[PDB]
Amino acid sequence: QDAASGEQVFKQCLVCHSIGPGAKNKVGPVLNGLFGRHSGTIEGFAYSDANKNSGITWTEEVFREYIRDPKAKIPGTKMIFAGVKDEQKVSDLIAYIKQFNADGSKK
Ligand code: HEC
Picture 1 (tube, rainbow, N blue to C red):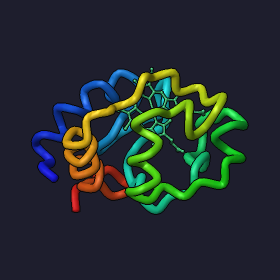
Picture 2: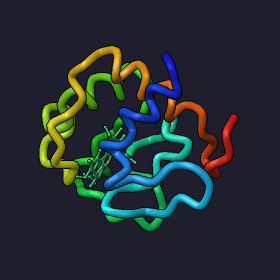
Picture 3: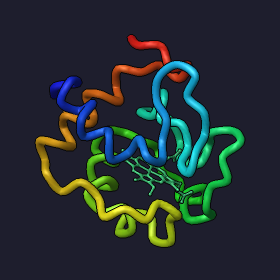
């Protein structure tokens, strides 16, 4: 979707997550290079067993389902957040996050 627009939806996430150059782990783990990565693998982040042992691979479709209702997808997750219900917002959000490489540089 529209990355400029996803940047604004990302503000809800920024409180707990970093993205971009120099991103560091906070309440939540860095989101650089998210798509394609296996859940619970950012080094130095203390993941819940619920996330670490889930066996999830972060594809766009799986991100989509998770973000609408995190607790429904990963019961017991430390990510206590109501989710993003709006379809367009999710599509924008995806566009924004997809811009980043694992190192925080922009594709
Ligand atoms: C604090 C109140 C959070 C907000 C707001 C958002 N996230 Fe989050 N996120 C948070 C925690 C504590 C964790 C770890 C969960 C655990 O159970 O260990 C997470 C995790 C994620 C993940 C999975 C990451 C992985 O490496 O597997 C994703 C994909 C994720 N968070 C995305 C995300 C987005 C897109 C948000 C904005 C809508 C967002 N989170 C908000 C804490 C918090």
